């Protein structure tokens, strides 16, 4: 898997963000995470603000596709997003603002990493695990 540059256009929700990738606007859905929905579930606005702040304040945004299918049925890209080297998917789970989702079409390179982060957020009874 390799990282590619992208530019933030607009954060839409805790699990979805619009990015300029290879010159064209595109909607990305964060791989392996399930965040409370804003469109409004409990912690939804917290998750949304977290994702937004983390990406708006970064110097560099990179996208990393996994080895499985790259887009869902709605046309959104399926990827791990990094903000200044830190993976947003992982930060959300670690902070207890998302649960790890079921592996989708072979996209599970970081499932264990995220699983570990979630167990810890759980032990700490953070946010969602409150």
Image: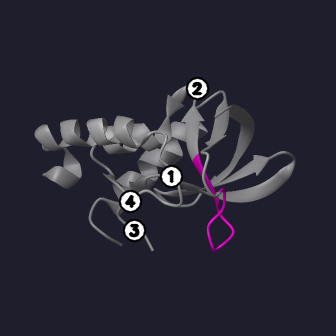
- Residue at image point 73% right, 35% down: 4
Is 77 covered by the magenta stretch?
A: yes
Earlier in the chain: of badge 3 and badge 1, it is 1
Q: Main secondary structure of the magenta part?
A: loop
Q: Which residue is mark 3?
A: 37
For disc 4, the marked residue is 102
Q: Residues within 10 Å of mark 3 (few under 14, many from 20)?
A: some
Residue at the limit of the structure toward the right, as seen here: 23
Residue to which mark 1 is pinned:
31
CA gap between label 3 and label 1 equals 15 Å
Percent across and percent down for residue 72 are 62, 67
Among the two numbered marks 2 and 1 on one chain, the one whose residue lies closer to the N terminus: 1
Q: Residues within 10 Å of mark 4 (few under 14, many from 20)?
A: few
Q: CA distance from mark 4 to mark 3?
A: 17 Å
Q: Secondary structure at mark 2?
A: loop
Q: What distance separates the C-alpha of mark 2 from that of mark 1? A: 18 Å
Q: Which residues are magenta?
A: 70-79
Q: How many marks?
A: 4
Q: x, y (%) of residue 48?
A: 44, 55
**Element marked by disc 3:** loop
Q: Position of residue 122 (x, y in %)?
A: 16, 44
The residue at the point 57 percent across, 60 percent down is 12
Q: Between label 4 and label 3, give the one nearer the viewer.
A: 4
Circles 2 and 3 in contact, beta carbons < 8 Å: no
Which residue is label 2 attached to?
A: 84
Q: Nearer the viewer, residue 50 or 102?
A: 102
């Amino acid at each position: 898997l390799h990282k590619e540059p992208a530019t933030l256009i607009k954060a839409i929700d805790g699990d979805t963000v619009k990015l300029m990738y290879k010159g064209q606007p595109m909607t990305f859905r964060l791989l392996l995470v399930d965040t409370p929905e804003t469109k409004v579930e409990k912690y939804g606005p917290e998750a949304s603000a977290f994702t937004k702040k983390m990406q708006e304040n970064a110097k560099k945004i990179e996208v990393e596709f996994d080895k499985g299918q790259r887009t869902d049925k709605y046309g959104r890209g399926l990827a791990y997003i990094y903000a200044d080297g830190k993976m947003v998917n992982e930060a959300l789970v670690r902070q207890g603002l998302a649960k790890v989702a079921y592996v989708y079409k072979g996209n599970n390179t970081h499932e264990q990493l995220l699983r570990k982060a979630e167990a810890q957020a759980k032990k700490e009874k953070l946010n969602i695990w409150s």
